[PDB]
Length: 80
Picture (cartoon, rainbow, N blue to C red):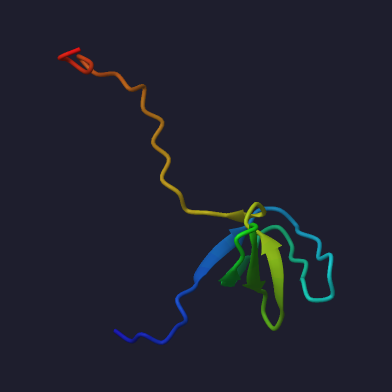
């Protein structure tokens, strides 16, 4: 292929976020954004079109694995 990116991940906004600082940017609920940077506090730098603001990973949807299994096993941890 062609490696030409700074290793980023695009997320989907599910909740309208409101910018608190002139730097941050507010986006509607139902759009896509690119996470440029990531803070250890939870605020990631996203880009919406021609603007870039720091939005909380809480408003952004993450593609995590969810497998709610009943944990039904014929047997348990034997030898105990």
